[PDB]
Length: 49
Length: 238
Length: 99
Ligand SMILES: *[C@@H]1O[C@H](CO)[C@@H](O)[C@H](O)[C@H]1NC(C)=O
Ligand SMILES: *[C@@H]1O[C@H](CO)[C@@H](O)[C@H](O)[C@H]1NC(C)=O
Ligand SMILES: *[C@@H]1O[C@H](CO)[C@@H](O)[C@H](O)[C@H]1NC(C)=O
Ligand SMILES: *[C@@H]1O[C@H](CO)[C@@H](O)[C@H](O)[C@H]1NC(C)=O
Ligand SMILES: *[C@@H]1O[C@H](CO)[C@@H](O)[C@H](O)[C@H]1NC(C)=O
Image (tube, rainbow over all chains, first blue to last red; front, side, top):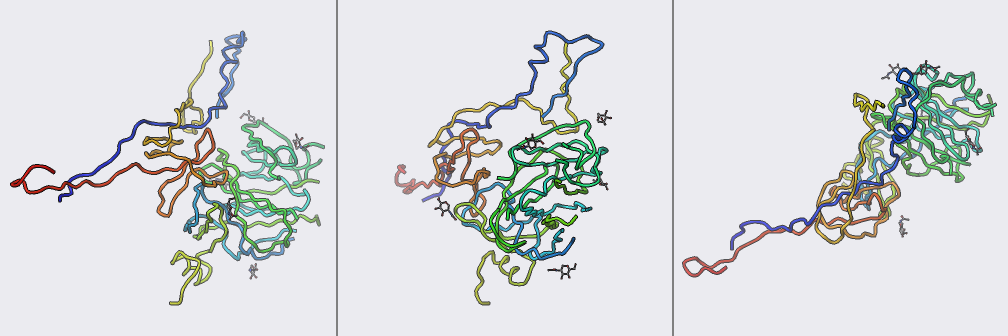
């Protein structure tokens, strides 16, 4: 009797389970505002986190 | 004002978020040495690695905390106020008044004025004879905070064991070399204590339910070190 | 016109795009990823009593054997898929060829 090799059951598929998505950064209001004042006086806001 | 007392077996918190059942995990982290020497206050206090703040403050008198470099409107600071419905954590600057007492007419009591505020996190009040224990830790700018509420009746600083849960891990990183307390309004019943954590080694005991029920310091006395070496709570003759 | 500068610099980013997910399959060998916990095995239903801040679970030898799913907060066991050795039984090739 000879011990030759090994033996395994292969995986079927793949799964990814990142948590719920929320706290979407605000970007529509910048695009959907109907006015940007002027090019010499523009509105800016910092978006982060 | 300062009267001192021993620390007994207090100030143990969950080191990580891993669930273990009926094991004995030997942990290496910053902790409060057993039978230490705390200062009972009846001020200027530095911040080297973390503190154990245990204000019983029976009704409501003590509230508020200031952390940072200069504790003024010059360098970034921190605030924590939890009254009855909301708690605020402002990371902006505030010059300091003469006393850390709240005016209760809106803000001029504890601090001077406001400026250029930034990220704010809110939550439910941290409150849920009324013992309150907190541990503050700032490592690589996550500002770990731990807490445990035991309004049960004991002594002014009794014995007993209670593990401390985590509470929040705010993404911060301001410089916190010094801090100072706050209150609302010296000869008052401002019963609270301080004490610095220390890099040590412990032996925490978990139960199948998942909660720490006992622990043993590994540098107190020879028997404790023997227990840690054997990784057990019992030792046979030898 | 708007200038949406995507500055990425020494300060931590903390501003990244979203991440989608897939379904949960139980009682089947599979690969998985739970917020960055790679590994393969069979996911079943467990009767453990996590405290409401504990994510993993570990044995006496530090092998992950429990996970709390992010979307739905329940407990799943983890058992690695089957493996073992293989031996071949033969008579002499001078005799026969069956095994
Ligand atoms: C604490 O420090 C004081 C001196 O500050 C010392 O007399 C005392 O033995 C120390 N330990 C305890 C338990 O009070
Ligand atoms: C933090 O502020 C203190 C003064 O409050 C200062 O001595 C120290 O150099 C600053 N930086 C660090 C890294 O502690
Ligand atoms: C606690 O303080 C905040 C801000 O000072 C206030 O909005 C809130 O109403 C206070 N809580 C109660 C119960 O009044
Ligand atoms: C607050 O921060 C802003 C921007 O960093 C700065 O212009 C201002 O001088 C600071 N102080 C006050 C009192 O606003
Ligand atoms: C953990 O929870 C189970 C189920 O309620 C309970 O039977 C057990 O006593 C608990 N463990 C304790 C209280 O140490």
